[PDB]
Amino acid sequence: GPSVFLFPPKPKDTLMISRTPEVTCVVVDVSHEDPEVKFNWYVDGVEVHNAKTKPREEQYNSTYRVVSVLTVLHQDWLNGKEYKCKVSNKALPAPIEKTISKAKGQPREPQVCTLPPSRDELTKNQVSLSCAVKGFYPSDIAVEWESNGQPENNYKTTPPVLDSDGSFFLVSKLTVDKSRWQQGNVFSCSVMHEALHNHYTQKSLSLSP
Amino acid sequence: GGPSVFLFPPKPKDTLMISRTPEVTCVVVDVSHEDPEVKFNWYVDGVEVHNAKTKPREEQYNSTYRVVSVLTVLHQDWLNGKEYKCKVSNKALPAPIEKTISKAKGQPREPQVCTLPPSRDELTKNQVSLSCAVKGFYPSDIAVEWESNGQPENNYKTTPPVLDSDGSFFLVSKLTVDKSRWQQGNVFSCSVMHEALHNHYTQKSLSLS
Ligand SMILES: *[C@@H]1O[C@H](CO[C@@H]2O[C@@H](C)[C@@H](O)[C@@H](O)[C@@H]2O)[C@@H](O[C@@H]2O[C@H](CO)[C@@H](O[C@@H]3O[C@H](CO[C@H]4O[C@H](CO)[C@@H](O)[C@H](O)[C@@H]4O[C@@H]4O[C@H](CO)[C@@H](O[C@@H]5O[C@H](CO)[C@H](O)[C@H](O)[C@H]5O)[C@H](O)[C@H]4NC(C)=O)[C@@H](O)[C@H](O[C@H]4O[C@H](CO)[C@@H](O)[C@H](O)[C@@H]4O[C@@H]4O[C@H](CO)[C@@H](O)[C@H](O)[C@H]4NC(C)=O)[C@@H]3O)[C@H](O)[C@H]2NC(C)=O)[C@H](O)[C@H]1NC(C)=O
Ligand SMILES: *[C@@H]1O[C@H](CO[C@@H]2O[C@@H](C)[C@@H](O)[C@@H](O)[C@@H]2O)[C@@H](O[C@@H]2O[C@H](CO)[C@@H](O[C@@H]3O[C@H](CO[C@H]4O[C@H](CO)[C@@H](O)[C@H](O)[C@@H]4O[C@@H]4O[C@H](CO)[C@@H](O[C@@H]5O[C@H](CO)[C@H](O)[C@H](O)[C@H]5O)[C@H](O)[C@H]4NC(C)=O)[C@@H](O)[C@H](O[C@H]4O[C@H](CO)[C@@H](O)[C@H](O)[C@@H]4O[C@@H]4O[C@H](CO)[C@@H](O)[C@H](O)[C@H]4NC(C)=O)[C@@H]3O)[C@H](O)[C@H]2NC(C)=O)[C@H](O)[C@H]1NC(C)=O
Image (cartoon, rainbow over all chains, first blue to last red):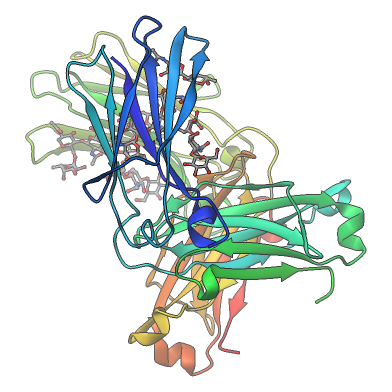
């Protein structure tokens, strides 16, 4: 009956020692008749108990969305440990077990390059600065924008795309007021990946050279 | 279980350059031995055309047939978003299979180019890769190439146009040269052909600086 989905820790969260990474176990199609879900967490086959039990969410299709969240400790997710979730419920003949771990294989650093505003864009009220992040592995990556030491949160980063070479590429687009770009303000592009030095790289772009 | 039709578009280079002749191809597969009669009808925006060359049937390795019809386009016709139909008729199918293609409708957007040099892992091996990121273009119809000192470099690979949240398209292109050629100081160019561009062309260069 119910379906189980196991989600990895937010890429930013696994890369900064100053964050709360957590694996997430989601159970959709839980009956209004048998709502209880017992969760069992395993870490490299060893049962852990620290999991956080989250209150069920009534979905509009008259079913519940039960979730459990196990916090990971950085040095474990990046070090390829296997996080197993065992979902037990009355409406299941036998428990559902799901497993997640970071993608194995040679870590490859991303390469960044920037795109200043377009020929048409520069005639509009708002302009867009873009970032191209190519050839990183695994797809676990954080793309943020910041200007003058302050977070610039009006951007859209595309989801990682696989290449014929076996690595990923994405595109980030920050949209800002034309007036700000013309004033020669300097906007940067932050990329976080396990293969970068100090897990981070940044690429600035302005009206100036 | 019957015959199958696939309708192919003219190459982006043929459509926006005085290079070769642009054609729209209609490929029919699974043509049975007992039902060989394949009738091809062509419609440019509703208007049936007879300037259609059908390549005599080809005996496939799995013992089927591959019948292909070719229609030549009057260059500007594809770019002007003219719709092409292929009504394939066969005895083996209950009713004719009609497939319709045209250049993607909606206002065009210019590609933005970005060059990336070799990475840390690349400059260790005998060969180095030089990437080229292209984004923001619409329609997907694009032609990416490489050339150095004027001669085309043909050991490259380009990803298919990926779709952005903002309905624009993007791709990355990777050229694999010899470390010695990059190291020598030689300059490599990324040639991007698209209708939204001025003179349907833009280049982007990189060298060892
Ligand atoms: C009743 O309705 C519910 C809900 O309705 C839904 O929502 C409403 C609003 C409508 O839009 C409606 O149409 C929707 O249906 C139904 O529930 C849905 O059920 C389906 C399956 O039946 C689920 O589909 C899977 O989605 C996965 C991705 O889910 C994410 O993205 C969607 C869409 O963006 C979101 O809605 C989800 O919430 C998920 O988002 C993630 O959520 C996490 C937890 O909140 C986040 O993680 C945490 O984030 C926090 C911060 O908030 C911290 O930072 C933590 O550290 C961090 O862990 C996470 O960030 C967030 N991400 C995003 C992007 O937002 C898919 O991956 C999955 O794919 C598989 O599906 C098929 C399974 O066989 C199949 O197609 C494939 O196999 C496919 O691929 C698998 O997965 C991976 C792929 O990489 C690979 O391993 C394999 O290829 C393959 N493996 C396996 C073993 O399968 C599904 O498509 C859907 O998520 C779910 N919705 C919700 C809300 O949970 C319900 O089904 C309906 N009932 C009935 C009877 O049908
Ligand atoms: C028995 O054999 C036959 C023959 O097969 C061949 O021989 C056997 C022995 C094997 O070796 C086999 O590998 C060989 O292919 C079998 O027939 C095959 O059947 C499958 C389907 O079952 C066909 O698959 C589709 O292919 C499309 C792409 O085809 C190109 O690529 C293949 C390689 O994979 C080539 O072999 C083809 O020749 C095609 O190549 C293109 O050909 C054009 C015409 O020649 C070229 O254009 C012209 O070029 C000249 C220069 O030469 C000029 O420049 C002109 O200007 C120019 O027009 C073009 O260059 C060339 N391109 C390339 C890339 O090479 C796929 O597109 C298609 O996928 C779509 O459809 C799927 C469903 O079928 C769908 O799931 C996908 O998502 C996808 O997209 C969707 O499609 C649907 C419609 O189908 C749409 O509604 C959707 O909108 C659409 N979505 C999107 C987002 O677009 C298929 O994968 C296969 O091609 C065919 N073989 C051949 C040779 O045609 C038969 O199956 C066997 N029997 C059995 C029992 O299996």
